[PDB]
Image (tube, helix red, strand yellow):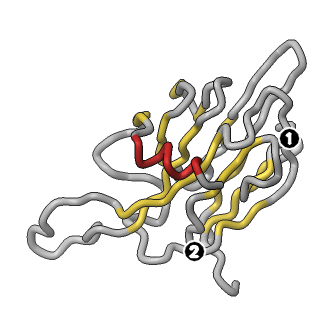
Amino acid sequence: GNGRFLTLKPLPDSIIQESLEIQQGVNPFFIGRSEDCNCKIEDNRLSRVHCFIFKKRHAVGKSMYESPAQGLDDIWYCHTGTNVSYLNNNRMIQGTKFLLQDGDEIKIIWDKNNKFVIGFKVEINDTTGLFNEGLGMLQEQRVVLKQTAEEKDLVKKL
């Protein structure tokens, strides 16, 4: 690859059926109804910036002895459109940050009335000095974080 690391693959089961490629963690990645977002999701009720994937350096403590995880870069999926974000079994709200482990198929919008369900498959082919292969294996186990002024600023400029 010329610079691939994370492939975001939305599929046919979800209203979004395309494949995106996050180059060595190209952040932030904007996602929503308008293709303007680095990621494409055609969902009427879904906001243009409704969801965005951001990358940050994994916050770790002093490297006691010789151990990996010596501070690296992690990717955080930050939802934003009122439809609330959904990953595995963690429910989110309109503006939450969540870790994306490999094989992360998240539904940004799910409506039984119109079957308007979304789903993206996170597949990290390359791990560029990442805190982990990308399967998320830190102390926290799939926890939802809140978006602060820092995240809100990312969506300010698509």
Query: Which x, y percent locates residue 56?
Result: 42, 60
Query: Which x, y percent locates residue 135?
Result: 48, 56
Query: Which x, y percent locates residue 12?
Result: 89, 43
Residue in the picture at 41% in, 42% down: 149
Q: Nearer the viewer, residue 155 or 142?
A: 155
Quadrant assignment, res 22: bottom right
Residue in the picture at 77% in, 36% down: 118
The circle on residue 34 is none
Q: Residues within 10 Å of mark 2 (few under 14, many from 20)?
A: some
**Element carrying mark 2:** loop
Quadrant assignment, res 141: top left
Residue in the picture at 62% in, 51% down: 103
- The residue identified by callout 1 is 42
Q: Which label's residue is closer to the chain start, 1 or 2?
A: 2
Q: Is 78 displayed left or right of 118 in the figure?
A: left
Q: Is residue 86 above or below residue 152?
A: above
**Amino acid type assigned to the residue bearing label 1 in the image:** Glu
- The residue identified by callout 2 is 24
Q: Residue furthest bottom?
A: 2
Label 1 to label 2, Cα distance in Å? 25 Å
Q: Quadrant of the N terminus?
A: bottom right
Q: Is residue 77 above or below residue 75?
A: above
Q: Is 119 displayed left or right of 85 in the figure?
A: right
Q: Residue furthest top?
A: 113
